Image (cartoon, rainbow, N blue to C red; front, top):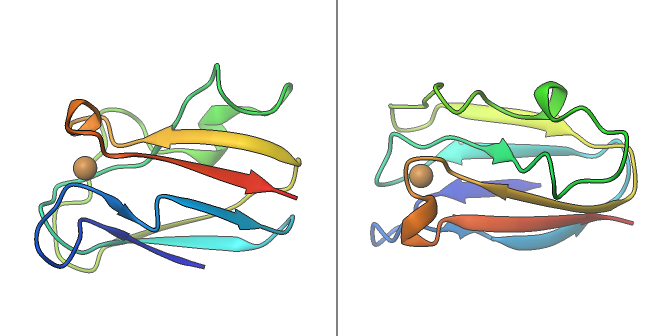
Length: 99
Ligand SMILES: [Cu+2]
């Protein structure tokens, strides 16, 4: 599935920000607008025994050009909360369920 970082009007949002995938399905996060952006999974808000480090960016890492992507595949089922670190307070957060 594809997920925009930033809406086409420059809003600080994931598009879409809530979605479900099947296990081992890849997510392509693409830098669209209002970057730099990143994608961090909340270590306290993912399925038990998942290593966040394996599925996220560092808080200190950035995508800073139009069309940079980050891709991940999730296999444990459950809900995964993520955010963009610099824009978290703007409300650039999301949630995926692996079902
Ligand atoms: Cu952002």
